[PDB]
Amino acid sequence: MEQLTLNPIGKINGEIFLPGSKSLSNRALLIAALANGVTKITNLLVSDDINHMLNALKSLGIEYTLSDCGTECTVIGNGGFFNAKKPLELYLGNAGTAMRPLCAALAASEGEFILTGEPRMKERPIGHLVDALAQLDADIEYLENKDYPPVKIKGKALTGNTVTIDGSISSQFLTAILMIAPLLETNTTIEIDGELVSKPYIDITLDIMRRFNVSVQNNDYKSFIVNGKQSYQALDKYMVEGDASSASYFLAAGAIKGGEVTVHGIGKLSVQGDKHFADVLEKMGAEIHWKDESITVIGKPLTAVDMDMNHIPDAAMTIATTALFATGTTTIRNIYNWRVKETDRLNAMATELRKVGAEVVEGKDYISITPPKSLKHAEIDTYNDHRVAMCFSLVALSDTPVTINDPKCTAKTFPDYFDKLAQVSC
């Protein structure tokens, strides 16, 4: 079907405004809906997943006003859990980051609810959440397949006390439990068996909760101590941070071909995991300046690195194409996570990199990249993966054009990517 050809960019320079991150947009919405008072949410993500969260909240009785074409939401807080007089079916599409938090809040609410989504969501397991909610006394039933949505929920006053949980495999469910637990009538102790995956995901959640006046004690991710009978308090203004993974492409472009780029939407107080990406560009020679709500990169000659990037696997992909512009052989280590996605991103990146003329070595969990003297013109297969398209856009910072197949695979996660890139291309 479609291809996009990007022609050689002589220089990158300018400002990029990142839209709100998906998962923080959902957390901001749910928290503001539960809070006491009026919150103005700014930089809210405009997308189909957020629109389902907005619709679910409207169904549940929450009053808000949208403005600036959906990027600003003034929410009148409900001051606690929801109350629906009639059975509601809430359809959350493919909104994974809304699904678990809402399931938790609805389990604590008064009403009867059916929670469902697209066939893609129905293949995402929910058993850990459901088991943790059952330890809080929740009443939830699988309507189709055991451990999968869709679910029927009869809301109850949940009782906290001791919740014992396994944090290897998934941490998404913990986030949902952390959000509701302060609002219960009892105190809650959450105990984690294993080593907990996705720590930054927990950090973001506890960070936004703290901004809405709710504290939880985190004991090194092995236990969480929660005081009950807390209440979220509305913020005058809350700006949804942009996605740090999305920042990576523009920071890399600025390091390679700048000029100066300032990415707005992510700043110095962010606790997103992929904020660590900037450190890799610094080790490569780029100059980085963190500011209150933005980060600035200034272009410098880059040198290859050999580093573990286990902590930032999405943004690490950006490093694989940035390596095409660095002196020496770049090695990205400890990225087995790339292999367990829909498509094996390790082999996919390697295959496309060889097409532009790089020498690439693939191991179980590393990739090693040696740039050619001159890049070759290629038609890049994107494997339905937004990240592959966005990484290989950086090839246009060479003397050679790049053709990207199926560029609309960006449409659901970052539709304006290519337009934003053109805004900073001179």
Image (tube, rainbow, N blue to C red):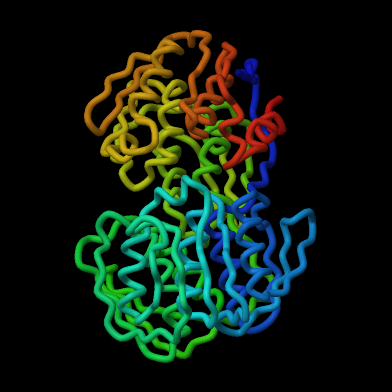
Front-most of residues 312 and 58:
58
At x 42%, y 32%, the residue is 319
Q: Residue 360, relative to residue 14: is it above or below?
A: above
Q: Position of residue 374 (x, y in %)?
A: 48, 9
Of the 4 image quadrants, the one containing the C terminus is top right
Q: Residue 70, relative to residue 392: is it above or below?
A: below
Q: Position of residue 303 (x, y in %)?
A: 40, 27
Q: Position of residue 324 (x, y in %)?
A: 44, 21
Q: Position of residue 46 (x, y in %)?
A: 68, 51
Q: Residue 196, relative to residue 165: is it above or below?
A: above
At x 23%, y 26%, the residue is 363
Of the 4 image quadrants, the one containing the N terminus is top right
Q: Residue furthest front?
A: 144
Q: Residue furthest right?
A: 68
Left or right, 282 with respect to 360, comes to right
Q: How many circles with numbers are drawn on the protein?
A: 0
The part of the image, by quadrant, that contains residue 42 is bottom right
At x 44%, y 51%, the residue is 122
Q: Residue 45, relative to residue 16: is it above or below?
A: below
At x 40%, y 48%, the residue is 123
Front-most of residues 415 and 160:
160
